[PDB]
Length: 67
Length: 66
Image 1 (cartoon, each protein chain N blue to C red):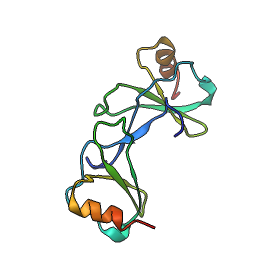
Image 2: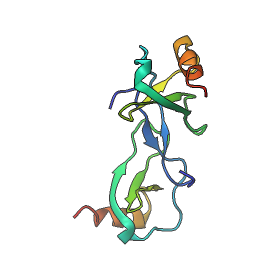
Image 3: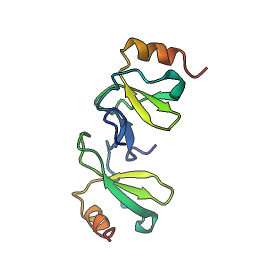
Image 4: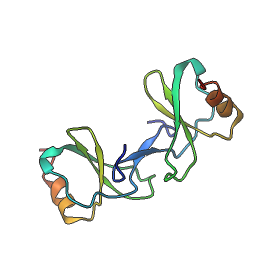
């Protein structure tokens, strides 16, 4: 949302084991307003999965989503 | 609702009360969020944050979902 007073998604736990890469189609980082600096993997059924950018598998997943 | 799925949080409350007729539903943001909040879901599907302690917010929720 463009509205300051509207909700924004935040993460409070990171997924431990990597979700199948083929089931992920997009990603974005949660707002800097959130307490945790997470990445969100958007799945095939549009689930918003939180992950830790510092973890190697997460870093590679993000890179593999480059154009 | 896995612990690792995102959940909506509020960081600012709408100051001016939005048109009550524009509201179709409401819910409370997770206690995991830093701020307590009532979210009014509008007919445009916006998720508007409001302060639960405000009089209008209280009277709004007391008269919705009926």
